[PDB]
Image 1 (cartoon, helix red, strand yellow):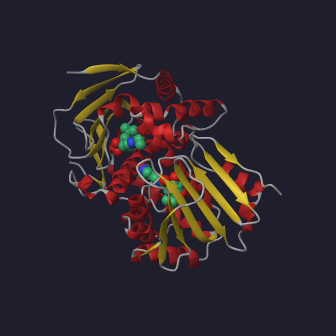
Image 2 (tube, rainbow over the protein chains, first blue to last red; image 1 turned 30 degrees about the vertical axis):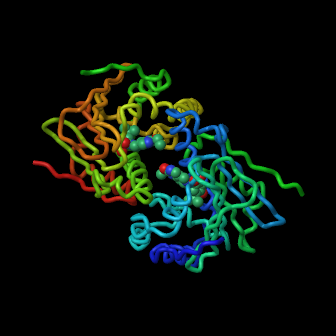
Length: 210
Length: 209
Ligand SMILES: CCOc1ncc2c(n1)CCN(C(=O)c1cc(C(C)C)c(O)cc1O)C2
Ligand SMILES: CCOc1ncc2c(n1)CCN(C(=O)c1cc(C(C)C)c(O)cc1O)C2
């Protein structure tokens, strides 16, 4: 059974902005996804400090980047805390964070789209390069879920039937036809090496089985 | 009343570096404290989307800067998720351990102190301008506490007796004698415009006199 939700009106607007504004520095999407992964990973390590059983679903804390030229997909996998169904639905579409209006405001007052992260809504920068985004997520308290959207004002949520994850969040970017550079080894390294924040977790870039 | 604790050795080490190294660009401390406040406010906002009862202790998500020239203090107050007693003593230091060590290594490879916030330990940049820092905090599940340190390798924690803050964290900088410029209204505005122009939450600069 697949459920369909409307994006909150301001979020639909943020997404349209992102998809339609001319902006050449698209590579910031990767930075924003890795920061989310970093926060999710901090969170599960933090909870494990007082309750070590939370790592029963997987004790390795890391980030994998997986390009697939055949599928034209770039996938980012982490083993952070993950999202329950309620987290998925509430944090990823149906409720506008105050940073959305604030961000869009800032754009009028002379900011760059690359600062989307300061406003807690960096995730939507994925649509700089992706025509469709699928998010698979597993939290300790819930079942494994699949979120999906090609924008257009709605997203769907279903129970995921694919390979279980143990715990964490996996972001599958279905790349636009002219954005395949982000499947190239040399390009991905370049963007990650440029990453401002010290990532306190191993980032492994997978090689394609060409 | 008051309990005294030893810093993690790497944090002690980082703190002596910050205090003893020659570095004129001290103003970056504000940017780092304002970044922490923003992160803290992200955390309670995130939690509140699924459990709105988390804002019972306070709906307003914002940051105050309060200079006091009588006391020679600069105070950064926010209404974020706040910190528990275990967070003050142990948890936060343990999470930041890998960044702390990584930062110190980076400095040896000739990087700049202003990069401190990139390694998740921007708070300790407070000791660029302060001889003593007092942190008052309130988390939803816990009581209100005072953390304190003048470096020298130790810190204290006590239950705070003062004004109940509801939820959040207040960082009181007791400024060095030669660092009073950061009490000046023009100077603070300048530094906020320069390094923190687009923060995701309102910031109110208090005026004096
Ligand atoms: C504010 C800190 O507290 C906190 N608690 C839980 C979580 C977070 N932060 C961050 C997000 N998160 C995830 O699972 C996650 C989500 C995204 C995109 C938004 C889809 C991503 O690209 C990678 C991820 O690991 C869970
Ligand atoms: C997920 C576990 O990691 C975690 N959880 C909660 C918090 C944090 N990290 C840091 C932020 N925070 C605060 O209270 C705070 C702290 C500082 C300085 C560090 C002293 C500051 O200058 C302003 C603040 O609001 C809350």
